[PDB]
Each structure stands twice: as C-alpha cells, then as structure tokens.
Image (tube, coloured by chain):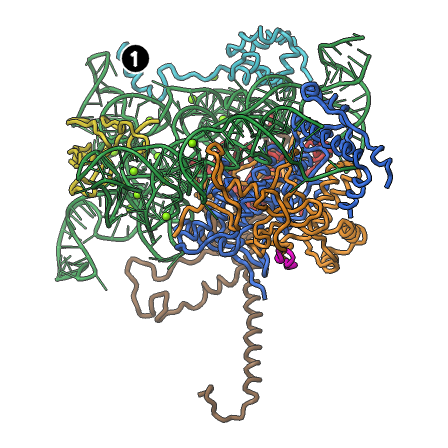
Chain colours: A yellow, B brown, C cyan, D red, E orange, F blue, G green
Amino acid sequence: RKACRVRLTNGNVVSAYIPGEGHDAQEHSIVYVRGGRCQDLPGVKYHVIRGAGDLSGVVNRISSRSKYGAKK
Amino acid sequence: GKGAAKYGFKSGVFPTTRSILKSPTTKQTDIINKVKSPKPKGVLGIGYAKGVKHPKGSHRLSPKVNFIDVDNLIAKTVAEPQSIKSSNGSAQKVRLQKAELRRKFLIEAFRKEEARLLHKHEYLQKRTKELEKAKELELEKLNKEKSSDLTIMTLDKM
Amino acid sequence: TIPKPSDQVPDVDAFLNKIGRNCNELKDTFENNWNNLFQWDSKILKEKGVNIQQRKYILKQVHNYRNNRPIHEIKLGKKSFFGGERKRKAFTAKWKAEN
Amino acid sequence: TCGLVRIRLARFGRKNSPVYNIVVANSRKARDAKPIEVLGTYVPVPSPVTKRELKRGVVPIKDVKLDFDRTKYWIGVGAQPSETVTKLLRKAGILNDAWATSKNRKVVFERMETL
Amino acid sequence: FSRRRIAYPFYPFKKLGRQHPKKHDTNLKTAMRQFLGPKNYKGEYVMNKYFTVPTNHVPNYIKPDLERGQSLEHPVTKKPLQLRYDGTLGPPPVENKRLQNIFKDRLLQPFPSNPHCKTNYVLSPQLKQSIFEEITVEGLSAQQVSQKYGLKIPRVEAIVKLVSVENSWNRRNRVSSDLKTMDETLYRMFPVFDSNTKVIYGELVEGERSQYKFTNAKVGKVGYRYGSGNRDNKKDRRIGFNKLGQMVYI
Amino acid sequence: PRKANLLKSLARGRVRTSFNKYNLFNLYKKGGVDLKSKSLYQQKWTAKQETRAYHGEHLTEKRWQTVFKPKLDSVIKETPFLLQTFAVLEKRLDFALFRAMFASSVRQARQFILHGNVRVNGVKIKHPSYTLKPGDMFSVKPDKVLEALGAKKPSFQEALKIDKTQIVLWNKYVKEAKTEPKEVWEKKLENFEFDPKWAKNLKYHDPIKLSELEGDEPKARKLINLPWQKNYVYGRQDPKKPFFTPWKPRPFLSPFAILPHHLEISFKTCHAVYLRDPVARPGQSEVISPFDVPVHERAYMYYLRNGK
RNA sequence: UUAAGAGUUAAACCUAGCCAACGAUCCAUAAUCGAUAAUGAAAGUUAGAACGAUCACGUUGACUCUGAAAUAUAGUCAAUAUCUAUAAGAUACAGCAGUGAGGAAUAUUGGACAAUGAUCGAAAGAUUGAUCCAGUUACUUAUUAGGAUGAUAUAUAUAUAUAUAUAAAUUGAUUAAAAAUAAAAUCCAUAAAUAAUUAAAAUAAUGAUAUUAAUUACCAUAUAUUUAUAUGGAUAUAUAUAUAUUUUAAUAGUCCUGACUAAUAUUUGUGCCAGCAGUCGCGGUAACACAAAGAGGGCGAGCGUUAAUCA
Ligand SMILES: [Mg+2]
Ligand SMILES: [Mg+2]
Ligand SMILES: [Mg+2]
Ligand SMILES: [Mg+2]
Ligand SMILES: [Mg+2]
Ligand SMILES: [Mg+2]
Ligand SMILES: [Mg+2]
Ligand SMILES: [Mg+2]
Ligand SMILES: [Mg+2]
Ligand SMILES: [Mg+2]
Ligand SMILES: [Mg+2]
Ligand SMILES: [Mg+2]
Ligand SMILES: [Mg+2]
Ligand SMILES: [Mg+2]
Ligand SMILES: [Mg+2]
Ligand SMILES: [Mg+2]
Ligand SMILES: [Mg+2]
C-alpha cells in the first residue's frame, strides 16, 4: 500500500494513504489531506485527495470518477 | 422556534408598550388604600420593627408613592392660551391650529387612560363579588347535604 | 396643459441656458419646441440620450416653471477648498508647509 | 422631522417588495432598530384591480393598519411625524391641513368612517 | 428476502417459445398483446372489454382476479373469448362463474387491491335543477334541501354554483356539440344518485390613482415583529399566491 | 420537477396517475403488492415505491418530505385511517384537475395549468402547486378537456389510408351482398337478434389514390361519400380542432373513470368545485388509490421517520 | 470627591476579620443572549453566521478639555509602522469597493439618492459607501426545466372481430432475459424570440433598478355577462375587399447493487497482485465485494466525500 508523510499548513505531520491505481506524488509535492484511515494499515489516519495539488486523477478511471478526480 | 411556543408561536419582539401615566392616579382608590394600609411586620414583613434601628445613613421607609392628579398634568403640561393676543400670521395661525390639535389629543389620551384603569378595576372587583355568590351557594348546598343526617358518627366524618 | 413662455423665458433654449447645470448642451435634443419640452416624461428623455442626473433636473425645473416658482440655477454642492473633512487636516498640513 | 422622538417608517419585507412599519423612534437610532413603539403597518403597493373594475368605478386601495388612539397620544406629546407619515396621517384625518406644505383640488370622495 | 422482481402477470399467460433471433421480443410485451388482442387497421383494440366505455350507468372496472386474466370479449355478442392453441381467439372451454358472481359493491370498486375506494354517484340533471330552483327561488335553506335529498350542504352549494354557471353558458349557448356529447357520455359511465373594527377611507381628490384605507389596530398586536425568524433559506420557506394568481413569498 | 422517464415500463410495473393503455396493463397485471418474506425495511421500501409511483411521481422526494403532514384527519366497519397519507396532495391544483377528469394525467394537468388554460375563482392560475381551499371553483378551457378525454386526431395521411381501407371493405360488403342478397339479409338479422331491392339500393364507391389525394385535404373531403362518414376524412370532420373531431371517447377510459367524492364536477362547462379535503370514514376513503391499507401504512411509517 | 451609596479613589484612626473541598485563589479558554438557527418525543444539547437586544473596541497605553453623558475613532504625551511637507508634520480602511499575506474557503476599486431614513438650511434645496438596487458565487431555499399517442413497411380485393401475403427486424438471450413505450414517427401546446402596448414601487413633481413586471398576438368601439356577432383604422392578395392575418422549441448528472442497505439478466480482465472498505470484511483461475460491459436501485441541478452539531 502506498502512503506518504505530509507536513500540513498548521504545522503538524501526518501519514496519508494515496488511493487509486496510480499515484503521481513524489517528494515535495503539494497535496490536500482529508480525514479517513486506511483500515488495514495502522497509523495512516488520512486520505490524500486525487485531483488536487500535484496529485492527478486516476488514469483511465471511468466509475466513481468524482472520488478519484477523473474527468468526463 | 421552541421558545416561541411559550408566547403563542410568535417569532420576533415588539418593543415593550409604554404607560401614558407612569404612576397611579388619585381616583384609583385601591392603590392608595394598599399604599396607606398598615404595613405588616413579622415572618412576612416589609419594614423595620418598632424598636429596631435602621442604618444611620439610610431612610427607614421607602420613598412615598407620588400619585398623579390627571387635572394637574393637564393643567401644567397642556394648559391653555391664557389670552387670545394674536394677529393674522402665515405661521401664527398654523402654529395655533397645530397646538390646539396637540392639546386636544393629549387631554383625550390622559382622560381615556384614567377611564380605562377605573373601569378595569371595577370590572375585576365585580367579578370577584359575583364569585362570592358561587361560594355562598356552595355553602348552602352543604346545608342540604347535612340536613339529612341522623347524628350518628360516620366514617367520612371520622 | 402647457404653460406659455414668459418674457423672461421666450423659448426652450432660454430655459435651458437659465437653469444651467451644464444642461445647455441639450438644446438640440429638444429642438427648441416649447410644447415637446412641456409634454414628455423621463422615458422619452431616456430614449433621447439624456443621462439620469440631467433628465431628473430638467423635470424638476419644468415643474418649477409649471407652478411659477423660480427656475434659477442652484449649483451642486462642492467640497471645501482645503478638502473633505476627513482629509482636511493632512491637506492643511501640506499646504501650509508649501507656503 | 426634528427632535428626539419621531414617527417614521421602518422598512420591512424583502428586496423589490417593500412594506413599512409605522414606528415611534429615537432620531439618533438606526432606521431598522427596534423603536419606542410600533403604531402600525403600511403596505405601499396598491391592491391590483381588474380592468373590468376600472370601468365599474372602484380604485386601488392601499392597506394601512394603525393605532388611532395611541398615535394621538404620541402626536400630543410632541413626537414629530415625517413627511410620508404626515401624508398618511393627514389622509386619515388625524392631522388637519395645518401640517400641509407649499410643495403639496376637487374631492371625488370625502373621507368616511365605517365599521 | 427482497429481489428485483420483473412484474410478470400474476395470472397464467402464453409465454414465448423458440423465437427467430431477430424478433427481439420480451414476455411482458406478449402479455400486453394478449391482454389487448388484435389491433385494428384504425388503430383500435375492439376485442378488449375495456376499449369501449359503458353506456348503461354501470361502471366497467378491471376485474383481473374475477376474470383469471382473460380480458377479451366479442364486441357485439359480449360473450367471452379466449386464446387457443390454434392461435385464433375462440370460445372458452368452460364458463367462468366468478364473472357472473360479482358483489354489488365490487361493481363500483375502481381498483381490485383497494376495497375502500368507491366511485361517487352522479346526480341526475333534473335533481340539480330541482335543488337550484328550491334554493334560489323558493328559498329553502341548504340545510333543508340537504335533509330533503340526503346530500351534504357543501355539495348542495357547489351544485347551486355549477347550475348558475350552466345557466349562463346555456343563455349564451357557449356549450358546443362536442361538450354535450362528452357530458352525455360521462353521465352514463357512473351510477345515478337516487333521492367590529374602525375603518377610515381617506379622501380621494381628482388625479389620485389609489385610496388609503386605515384599519384600527392595537399596539403590541400591529406591526412586523423585530427579530422574526428568517425562513427564506430553509425548506419551510413560506409561499403564497396574490389574488392575481402570482406566486409571492408570504 | 422530476423529469419523466420510464414511467410506463412493464418490467417495473408501477401504476401511475394516468389513463394510458400501458398504465392500464400495469394496473391489471400487478395483482397486489407483495409484502411477504420481507424485513420491515424492505416492506417499507416496497410500500414507498408502489404508493409514491402513484401519488406524486413528479414531486421531488425532499419536497414531498416537507409537504408530508405527519398529522392526519378523520371525521361496524373500520375507518381506514392511514389511507389519508397522501390526502395532502389532493388539494393541489393539478391533482384536482386529474381527479375531476379534466386531464388524462397529473403531468397533463400540470401542462394545462402552466399553459394558462386553468382558472380558480375566475383568476388565471399558472402554477401547478396552487392549493385549493374548500368551496373553490376551478375551470378548464373546454377544448383542452375534450382533447384530454378524446382520441388522438389522426394525421392527414393516416386517416387517408384508413379511408382507403374503409372504401375497400365497403366495396367488399356491397359486392358480397349483390352476389347473395337474400341470405345476407337473413344472416344480418341473425346477428341483429325478403326485399331484393335491398342490395339494389346499396351503391359502390371508387378506390382513392394516395399519390393523387396527397396534400389536398379539401379535395379528399369531397371525394369521400361513405354512408357513415359523409364528406370528411376519418377523424377530421373539422381539421382545426385539437381532437378526433366526430368526438369519440378516448380508448381505455372506463377503467380509470372514478367520480371523486370531494369534488363536484360539471362536465358540460368543464368546471368543478372543491367541496372538502378528502376524509376517511368508516369503511371508505376519499383518497382514490390503487393500493390497500397495509401498503399505505408501511409508506406512512417510512415517511414518519424519513426512512430510518 | 460626585448629582448620588460604597475601601471606588486619596488622607487619618480603630477592630480582626473576609473567601474556601457545594471548590476559594491561580491558570487556560470565551464577547453574552432571544419570541434567532440546528436537533430531539421531550428534558435538554449545539451555534451565537444571518434577523433582533446588550456590551467592548476603532493600531497600543495613560491622562486632559468640552459636555448632562467620553479616559471620545477628539486633544496631549509616549509605543509600533509607514509616508513627505522634515514640522511642538500627516497617516493607521475592524466605513464601502479593492490589494497583498494567512487559509480548505467567503464577492463589485458597480448605479442612484427614485424610495425609507440621517445632517445642514427660513426656504429653495445640498450631502449621504447609511440605505435602496444591481454585479459575482448552486452557499441555501422555492418554481419551472413538454404533454398525449406510439412496436414495423409495402401489394391485393349505415357496414363494421377485415383477411391475406411477402419483406425486413439494433444490443443481449433461447424464454417467465431483458434493454424497450425506451427511440423514431404523429397530434397538440407553451417558453424564448418579434411586434405592440404597459402598470406598480410615488407622487405636487421626482424611477437607480430597467432592454420593468404583466397583458394581447394586428388595432380600437358597442353591446351582453371570460366568451362572442357587429362598426371603424391595419393587412398582402388577386381583382374599395371574398380571403387570411409573426414564429416557435427541448436541455441531466452523480453515487451505489455480499450483509447492515433499496438494487437477480448476465458476462469479461486480474488472481492475497492491482486494489476496495463506515462495520463485518473481499482479492490464490467460479470474484454478486478490485477494474469493467450489460441490466438495475437511490437522490437529482444536484450527487458523493471530508469536517463538525443533534438524535
Ligand atoms: Mg451655495
Ligand atoms: Mg438487498
Ligand atoms: Mg476572545
Ligand atoms: Mg459559548
Ligand atoms: Mg470577543
Ligand atoms: Mg449575530
Ligand atoms: Mg459576516
Ligand atoms: Mg474607545
Ligand atoms: Mg487596522
Ligand atoms: Mg484604545
Ligand atoms: Mg473594507
Ligand atoms: Mg433620498
Ligand atoms: Mg456612490
Ligand atoms: Mg444478437
Ligand atoms: Mg468503489
Ligand atoms: Mg459494497
Ligand atoms: Mg433546488
């Protein structure tokens, strides 16, 4: 499972699960973090938003497009 | 929305309605009687007892209630043109007519407010006096209840 | 009804020049016709290209002429020379420094 | 309008559909703040009338609800009505022609009081 | 256990068999066709019992349970007709006794599933005229007429108003032949019923476009209250209709 | 409001407030609502589906929830109290039109209202949501009522072909009558339960040509002389009226012809009076519905809690 | 001292008290409230945006004048930070627009004083970023956002169950497997547009909004009580007058279908990987749970998700 370490704008540091088939997030990328924990992974309490910042929508996504930042 | 249910389900407040006469009028005898009645001292008392001392810099009894005399207010506030000294004036006649209307309106207001207070008090007193009839007829109905009694002690009486 | 020209006010152009307020630019729009000046309302003035402040002012002065009250110009209020009350102190400080 | 106590109209309703509240208020206080008293309501818009009713002879009616006895009390004390309130009260007969102004002939319908 | 259940007919019907691949048909369409019957060149479905309205003051409502799903009948003889293995509509094997055994109320029941629903009776035009004459002319109050004819007061008042409108239309002959035909048709489809404050109006001088009307009211009861709840951005937004019929926010 | 889609699908089999043939079949084949072998939530959902398909399909769900009145009104048999779940809708103007038989659907009544054909107490109301008070009188333009309760006006081409076929069959009948007249008369009497001039009186008719009659309706009007339709194309006596002009009741009208209790109707003038709000009484409910009390009570329990 | 009580402030002299485990003192946090909003069956709980009431502040602190009322958005002094005019200077946008920063995120450097108010003036009238209007933004709510009919296409010859042929017939499937009356087609409307006219907000007159709402589909009058037949100005035509009298539509997403939990018509790809997931949990060649096609179930100009409140 793909997760990232994210320093937020309030100053805290969190662990965020990157959903979707493919992540375009590298180090020093700008992301937006929402609540929600990766249930089967302890310590990742947050979800990175797909379609915001430097995270793009899931490529070739056609169902539940909104949740994954896809366009159509 | 819940609190409005206390007031007839009315949302929003009007300003509190003002009183034309701020103090009771002289003709309103009942308030004078309560005011000049003997002051009770005891378990439920309102004033310092006979031998009790009040603080050196305080007044023993509360300020006297100043009872309005409607005629006095009408004479001092509204008054009347003492003399008819005047001439034709574009502003003089206008101001005289304005002042006459205001005089009439305030006189009518004061008199009507006194009248409503008097009539209302008489109304409440009357209602109580008719309720006295209900009490006395109930007592009479108790007579006929015990008119048919054979003087033996009875459980309800025990 | 229409009120007749006075000897003070022979024609429409006299009225426009007298009332002032830069209204004398509207001579052409009225075509010097007294009757048309005293017959149409602000909808026609709006169509004819008169802007808001003017058509309101000319209707005011037309009413004044109808009821015989004078139609002399009253200049719109201007701010003080030193400036508005809020900026007056700073402007006076600067102006006194320059003189 | 002058003095501390003034009888005015406070704007209630929504955008593009005014109604007004005949109030007795401090001059120095805001227009829409709670006043000393609320003497009435005034709906400016005339009641629409059918084209037939224009021929029959009725006219649009504007609805004013007012406390006549209390407004007399406030006028007597020296509360100063505003121009619009002056116009309304003068039509009501509460105020006579002494309150008329130079800026302001025949009577088709004279004022009538009914129950 | 809930299942997405395709609404197949409860009664038995002749289902599809081996089909030409290009038919592209569904059982529901076959049920539709069997319920209707053959389609006429005019577009009608004469074979059905429900294509044509009744004309003897006895409403004809669907009775699928009492019919066992067979809804075809001879348009003239009115005897039942049912599908056959030959493929041509023909007489039934046996009489359906339940079509004969119809309860008196069930004849007036629109929908089989809802027994409480029933169709109101149509008043005879003579009765409407009698009510109109009794109230308008003789002066008998709506109470007396309602007691007389076993009707309700509001229905009586509605009858009077409708007969007034009918009188005006008849006076102008605004009724047309199509309207009369529809009236006579609908009439025969239903069973026939068997017997103070101070107000000041201000002065209106010439040129005034409207008249102020002043109504007496008491302080603490007159006004728009301050701090009233704003419901415009809420689901309970209050809406009314001006007397012109324009929707206004009340 | 809701965009109408798949309202009359046979697979779904939901009955709608309509006089349509497909709606008639959907009502026919349903039988009764199946609430058995279902949890309480599933019973409530099925009741919602069935009842909400009929009573207010156009109403939005979040709007119906606000309109829904949790407190009902009721004035030996049993009172069906919970059939009044949807009685609140019965005072809406469009529902009043549909119940008065002034429209073939609630959506058609809505279009009638929005297109200015409806009046309530003599003022033109253009809003379907207008609520009727008791005693109100509302009227619809008679042309639209006749269109609602009448068959579709055929196109010129369709009626022309229908006339072609009618001429063909009339010629066939007169031919067979001429060949075998006596027994033709006798066997016609056989259904109805000799004069040789009978077949002589009957007269042929000339087959028309679509190509030559196309686009000339006044000519086609003169060219037809059938005994039953003399000088007018089928269904187009006056081609400038919105309905089948030799006025004919629409097909499949008897199933849905319910006379409501709460309304008093005048078909001659296309007027109606709203007597009262529908009220349940012992053994009878004035809310015309195709569903039984259990379905309505399940829907009522659904809407009381809003699906909880 | 004050108009006025009081260790409120200043002076003097006495007594030893006062508060506190039903929580003092201290610390942290917070503007408070309603006939306001949310929620609940209710008690209550939450918010204090919007409507209204009270208080405090107008870059920070202290003091002074005036005054009835001020530690005033005043004055003096100082602090912070900028500008020039370099002076016992000015300014501090928590007034309306607007800019930069911070933020997940919250608009016009708009029009008019026409209305309702405020100030000045005797008056005419002047000013009004209050206010009224409009602009942007689905942030919220409401109304509209099209009804009826509709499973075939050709050929044959006062009645009426018209019948025969041929031809085709998209996706899935071989029957209770459907998509689907859904399309197309037909009938009839209306919105918009185009013409006229046209209120009301305001009257003595004044209309920003405004290319006004609304009404009629040529225009009036003349009678009846909305529908009509008439008289008179339009109207192109053909040849003053028989005729008709603008045109006209259609525009839906987003989530989900193992149970909770509504969603049976089935197939494909992957194979404890990719991935999903609110809880149970799913994924090893047969996945109803991942990624999809078909079908289906919600809500719908919104749908889902996150964050919070109540239950
Ligand atoms: Mg000057
Ligand atoms: Mg399920
Ligand atoms: Mg704070
Ligand atoms: Mg708090
Ligand atoms: Mg604070
Ligand atoms: Mg607030
Ligand atoms: Mg704010
Ligand atoms: Mg301060
Ligand atoms: Mg600042
Ligand atoms: Mg300060
Ligand atoms: Mg600002
Ligand atoms: Mg102004
Ligand atoms: Mg401005
Ligand atoms: Mg295939
Ligand atoms: Mg998913
Ligand atoms: Mg799932
Ligand atoms: Mg909405």
In the rendering, at what x and y percent does residue F164 appear? 70, 27
The structure residue drawn at horizontal position 62% and vertical position 12%, both measured from the top left corner, is C37
In the rendering, at what x and y percent does residue A10 appear? 19, 34
The structure residue drawn at horizontal position 33% and vertical position 20%, both measured from the top left corner, is C87
Which residue was labeled with disc 1?
C95
Residue A50 belongs to magenta span: no
The amino acid beneath tag 1 is Trp
In the rendering, at what x and y percent does residue G13 appear? 13, 55
Quarter assignment of residue F115: top right
Taking the view exactly as shown, the residue that stands out farthest to the front is F179
- In the image, G252: left or right of D18? left
Chain to which mark 1 belongs = C
- In the image, A30: left or right of F186? left
Q: Compare residues D39 and F147 and report the one nearer the observer.
A: F147
Q: Is mark 1 within 8 Å of ligand 1?
A: no
Q: Compare residues G282 and C50 and report the one nearer the observer.
A: G282
Q: Can you tell me which quadrant of the image ligand 7 is in?
A: top left
Q: Which residues are the magenta region?
A: E96-104
The structure residue drawn at horizontal position 70% and vertical position 38%, both measured from the top left corner, is F248
Q: Compare residues E66 and E59 and report the one nearer the observer.
A: E66
Q: From this view, report whether residue F261 is shown above or below residue G244.
A: below
Question: Residue D105: in sight, yes or no?
Answer: no
Question: Residue B128: in sight, yes or no?
Answer: yes
- In the image, E83: left or right of D59? left
Counting every numbered tag in the picture gives 1
In the rendering, at what x and y percent does residue G302 appear? 41, 36
> Are there few (<14), some (14-19), or many (20+) residues within 10 Å of tag 1?
few
Label 1: state its secondary structure: helix
